[PDB]
Image (cartoon, rainbow over the protein chains, first blue to last red):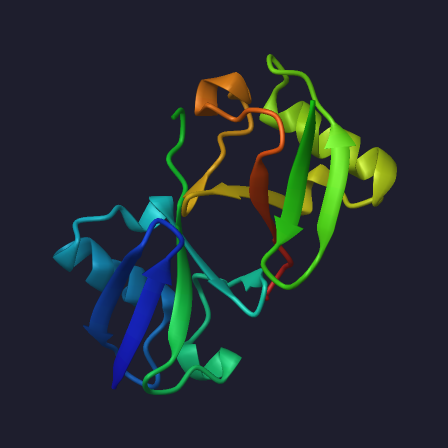
Length: 76
Length: 76
């Protein structure tokens, strides 16, 4: 299923995630494409932060959904 | 100087911070006001998270600047 991860920096990411795909694997996809380190990725939804060990369907995340991405660069 | 702390959900907090203030200290000041624990305070600037150990002027944060605040809850 397609999803749209938009960051406040002004960048959107389009990935084909799976219903039972863990948040951890979602970050992995971004890492594969944009090359953004999953450990530096902060997926925010509804105003809170998502848990790496959780699934998309855990937060009612479906197709065409929008996830907020924040770059957490450590030491800078 | 005063800055604007706006959450991703909907809230605008205003406090007095120094140019050489630290992100960690900023969260501490917000805790003295809104009572929100600094551990749950996520400072966002242009889609990038603010390093807790960095300074406001290091991020080019001046007076009357608006920052985003995200609540980091466990499990979301």
